[PDB]
Image: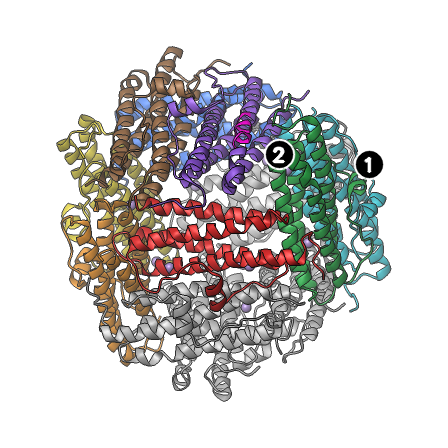
Chain colours: A blue, B yellow, C orange, F red, H brown, I purple, J green, L cyan
């Protein structure tokens, strides 16, 4: 059945392309957070195990909301290692860094996602897509909050 | 007691007029969806009965939220058959269509509400009512997501 | 599939027609109650706002149970403004009455549903349909209780 | 301790006999519904696996409610394969029907129990046993609704 | 405001009177079960302390439902020691019986409520007060069930 | 088994006697509150019906707790219309006052229970019984709270 | 679709056959427990009525789990009076035994399931069906624990 | 660690300054609402006690949400009587006014927070901070809705 | 309508006055703890953010309980910045201290409330206002427990 | 950091010593209640297994609250076999008594702990330690109630 | 701190290696299931969207359990696209297959995890790592059960 | 009543001996963890007070499960300081060590329970006591997981 939601097909394709990078970034940050949840050690173990658990649990929900916005725009949601490797601007950590470096990478991850969200608004303006803009706004809120909580641990 | 929320009375009345049409369209969709929930048959009965139940439940809450924004703006919320028939842009189904045609009508219903929501933004531009804009954006989000779920059923 | 529940076709039809009137009254009362829930003002705002909330919430469940009794009997459940306007015995209010007039209208609404339910028992006796008689009994219980709470506000 | 609930011992024995057949039909339908839940296949697996689970779960409670009404009347509740095979009017399915034949057998199961329940209201009439009449009424409402949901799948 | 629930004023007055006696017997049984919950002793303490708890908990709700049916009919609900002793047909226990005698009195108490309930159905036949008839049926069902559970301890 | 809790038989018996007046006042206030819940009318119906419900709900748990302190002290908990009408200092109301008068009686009822609890303290300040002292404290806290909420309605 | 879970058709068939006996014993025990739950009398009514409720509630879940393991192995799950009566090793009880004999039979029921469970293990080692082995293990744990709680009543 | 969220430091300081006045007005209204909750009296006591309780509970969460947006922007959240008295645009009530005047001041208070929220938007246009805009929008929605509920009490 | 709860006006007023001071210390500690919850940083961010959250949540309920005892005694409960500044004995912190100083101040705050509570008892002994006595006793138990948990963090 | 709760070190060390015996009694009773829960047999198995479970569950919480009041006072909490063995006035039971004797020993235990509670109140008076006085008062309330329920089994 | 759990470093490392492949397969099945949840269309949208939701939700918990078992063995858990792609035996789908093909791949994906689980058991036998054995057993049980439900949709 | 679960009395007694040791190690760890929960200090207070709370809460449930496995085997469960101190292989700590030494001891407690569980397995091979093997497996899984979390804190 044809889609008549007030946005033409190529404009929807462009928004979906942006949301696909956002999904890729969000999912890469999900897996990294999950990874650090399992692997962190040192005297901060209990606090960071729990903190990273709260984060990966939140991100798992965010990946589902982003992917379904893509579907609501009429396009397939990417969901493979190859697609996420290709589309993600966040780099993965292949080793087991010290707790402090883990916190530092996650701060940078939050901020990388904010960057990707900001990059999509020029498009939404010209095309007019308030739901997508509200989605990006919610992700920016969560990641900026999460970044304050993470960097606060590094404060002198 | 005089209302001092930063919007003049005739501008509030224009917004309320717009939200009254959105409320009638949402209410008409609610009862149609409820109707189809009762009356659908065929091998998709269990899945459509449940699916339309989720939708009518969500719309029941949406009708209350839209009505209460009208009240927040200092105007009465319409709430009769005659007001909704007059204000709605969606047509009712008096008979019992096939399940496929139920699904198609509900897809068109989602899209009709999105169009009514959009028609209110030019007003909100000129006037400046962020809460109402957030409400329209939420309804657009729900209806565009529901449209994807409904139209997926028809894919061949 | 054939319907073999011990009630014949014309009989089920006549019961369904009675329940359609009850559904139409119940649904009209639901919307009137929803409407007064939004629009009531005055010093009783908070209690009436909340009380009309409990009522429309209960009525929304009752509409689903009446509708689905109609379906168990083998007939489509009506569900449009036109069908309810034709079938319904409750006069609609297009303005915003004072709080005490809203209460009276709702009392009269409760009693209209009861009057419609009572209107169906003569048929049910003849026909024998204990589930529908029990549905009508449950609705009469609710509407009579709700009528006492409403009219109590007017004393 | 003697039982003085306003119904004599042989009248209670007779109500217990009717309830014992109702219990055997309800229990046979419970096990068949449980069987079909486990064994149904095809594209309707997810929807029927779930639907038959709602039904068999509802029926486990019904068996306990019927059986304890028999106890309330002063009589033992039957509860063996042999007892239920003897009292049941519902035929058993020893194989694995296609999904549609499962839906159809279960519609007829619903209508069988309603038949058994209807057969009992004469007696309860004569001896004015209002609890047992309410129990039969609730079982009929359930099975008639279920039969509509089942048969809707075959339309 | 006028009461127009389809039952004239004199008929409601008489049903209200029946229910007032049902309420007094239910409340009296309520306070006796409560009394025995506190006061039972012996090797059955745990079983009966808990069993009598479930019973008074249930009856507390029963008294509220009965009283509000009276209110729905347009009449004040009695609720003093003096009204209940006058209206009650159950006699209270001023002492502290042995466990077995507590059980026997509670059994008898269940059957006394069932009796007061049956006393009422005649007033309902004339006017088809189905809500009240369902209320009585539910109380009869609860007390007949509880009688079985209590009397079972004496076998 | 002998009760060895560091309070002597006569002293316990004197506490039981005081707690028994507390129970009688609490139970009499419970039933008065219940009564007024059912019977209040007027524009404040919703607020008072709900307010009195919360009050009566809380006292029912309190009667159980007062009564079980008496049993902990080795004595029977009173539980009859006669025994409460004797011990209670709450004048019962046999008719249906105006809502404002219901509120006043209920205020006085809170104060009555506190007056009784206070009367029991001399006895406690000669015997060492911290649990009974804490129970009296909890009741006074609740009834003084309740009295403020009640009297506020009258300002 | 072919089944490739690492066990070949014949072995899956042999394991499903043992699980079918386990299902039958478990289901028969379920019904006998359900039966004794309804039918026990005497001083221990309250305690055995609840104890047998807990057990049959657990066994109803167990029948589902065993049946679905049979489906996971690729075979249909038996589910008729005739099929359980043939496969079961538990003797049914058509009467109403005394409370202690009900306990005694339910003890022996637990031990017959264990016996059946143990008979299946030789087969599983051969093919290393670990999920089936864990299933048997959990049922044995539950039945051994229930046995202890039941026989404790007879010490 | 450097803050790289796409907003410069002085731009963040200006947003934080605006949000610090939003926080001060929100906290001042929280406390005023809490105060009126404790202190209101008259026949509306029950409904305003509860309504003001809904409001202060919601505002308590709002104060935490606003303060943590400030922290997300990299600045300290104000949290003293002196800081809030300096930054607040809302005056406190030091006495105990009549219920109507309490309602009037809470209306004025809702509308004061809306004006403060509105005042911050020009900054967010120029700078680009969508999260803060969404926070402002949610506060505006809550206070405008609450203003309707409150002022409806005065119609 | 009169108040006859076995205590006279002049005595209730004296108790209300002492509970007014308790309310003011409890609120000032409430606000201080909330402040530290938002504002604490360092490697202990997570544990202290969470710990101060539990405390400010508890204290919010205590202020409601103290305030309504005053009301039960027949007097208006104070609730303004100025009323609490005047009546309170806790020193407010206008800055953002290091985490260890935040802990130390919150210990002192616990003890300050206890000190205020002890000072009221004499006045209850005369008239046997047992409810107020039990209220004080409960606050003392919470604050002394909270003080132990706080000071255990400083131990070396 | 220094402790300044209005109670000097010597007085706090004396209270700790008392609470340390109360804790060793409470714990010893906790393990003994726990032990009898596992090991009781006979026809009261179900009722006592469940009664002892409720009791030990309660005692496990009480041990934590006693230990942590000892930390609030500024002293370590004992927590080993040797410490509890040294401090406990509760005699341990190394075999498996019969149910009646288990009931007896647990009644003794409730009363032993009440006795230790009482022994500490003089200190608390001297120094005014109201929190610890309320802890003891709560233990005594629970143990005196529990003893009533246990000894009731022996009547 | 040294790891002394009865298994040496080299053996723990070999098991960790095996569990790393189990993690990779399980995470790959996780993401594919998640993908088919978003992307499936056609008449089965509603049932498959929900079924795949239940599956991916269960696998999210499973990956956490397998990861933490590797950590309990003393080794890092892998957690990157490259590491999972290297270790996984499941082939990713880069397109959007038809619903039936999605079902078919999810069946094979269930069977591939079982295949990997089986391959690990020898290394466990030679050292008596019973917790890892039980983890593998639980995964096989979930996956064989899920394969039955999936393949049933294709009959 | 004889015990017939497939294991001889000599064998069941030997298994109950192994589990008595396990029960003793588990209770000893339980109390030590509970002790450290109360007594730990320093900058890790909040994290370790919480972590040790979760651990003792879990071990308290574990002791009940191990005790009741012994009762399922037909032997009494030990439960006194002297029985546990005799059987326990875990050396207690009578002082208050530094937080890090508390962690290290709790690591060794975990591994000591694992050591005792492993000693028991042979005796279960000879006999096929599957429930007991699974209980040990579960305990091993919990302790080896808790060990990783605890030793992680020391990295
Ligand atoms: Mn989803
Ligand atoms: Mn609403
Ligand atoms: Mn429905
Ligand atoms: Mn039952
Ligand atoms: Mn009521
Ligand atoms: Mn009780
Ligand atoms: Mn199932
Ligand atoms: Mn916060
Ligand atoms: Mn409050
Ligand atoms: Mn603790
Ligand atoms: Mn985890
Ligand atoms: Mn246990």
Answer yes or no: is residue H121 visible: yes
Above-or-below relation of B15 to J49: above
Task: Determine whether the residue tagged by mark 1 lies in a helix, strand or loop.
Answer: loop
* Residue C80 in view of the camera: no
Helix, strand or loop for the magenta stretch, by majority: helix
Classify 10 Å Cα crowding around label 2: few (below 14), some (14-19), many (20 and above). Answer: some
At horizontal 36% and vertical 58% (from top left) the residue drawn is F37
Cα distance between the residues tagged 1 and 2: 40 Å
Q: Secondary structure at mark 2?
A: loop
Q: Is residue C141 above or below residue C39?
A: below
Which of the two residues, B10 or J101, is positioned nearer the viewer here? Answer: J101
- Quarter of the image where one finds residue L43: top right
Q: Is residue I37 left or right of residue H95?
A: right
Q: In the rendered structure, are the residues bearing label 1 and label 2 in contact, judged by CB atoms less than 8 Å apart?
A: no
Quick check: J47 left or right of A116?
right
Q: Which mark is residue I68?
A: none
Q: Position of residue J71 (x, y in %)?
A: 66, 32
Callout count: 2
Q: Nearer the viewer, residue B152 or I92?
A: I92
Callout 1 crowding tier (Cα within 10 Å): few <14, some 14–19, many ≥20 = few
In this view, A12 is above or below F144? above
Label 2: chain letter: J
Q: Chain of mark 1?
A: L
Q: Along the line of sight, which residue is nearer the eye, C1 or C8? A: C8
The magenta segment is I112-120
Within 8 Å of ligand 10, the CB of disc 1?
Answer: no
Residue F84 horizontal/vertical position (percent): 48, 64
Determine the image quadrant of residue B47: bottom left
- Which residue is under mark 1? L91
């Amino acid at each position: 059945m044809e889609i008549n939601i007030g946005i033409g097909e190529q404009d929807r394709a462009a928004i979906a392309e942006g949301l696909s990078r956002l999904l890729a970034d969000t999912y890469t940050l999900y897996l990294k957070t999950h990874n650090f949840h399992w692997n962190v050690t040192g005297p901060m173990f209990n606090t960071l195990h729990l903190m990273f658990e709260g984060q990966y649990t939140e991100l798992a929900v965010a990946v589902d909301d982003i992917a379904e916005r893509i579907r609501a725009l009429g396009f397939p949601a990417p969901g493979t290692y190859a697609a996420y490797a290709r589309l993600s601007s966040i780099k993965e950590e292949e080793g087991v860094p010290e707790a402090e470096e883990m916190i530092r990478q996650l701060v940078q991850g939050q901020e990388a996602v904010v960057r990707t969200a900001r990059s999509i608004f020029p498009l939404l303006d010209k095309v007019s897509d308030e739901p997508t803009a509200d989605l990006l706004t919610q992700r920016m809120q969560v990641h900026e909050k999460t970044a304050w909580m993470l960097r606060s641990l590094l404060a002198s």
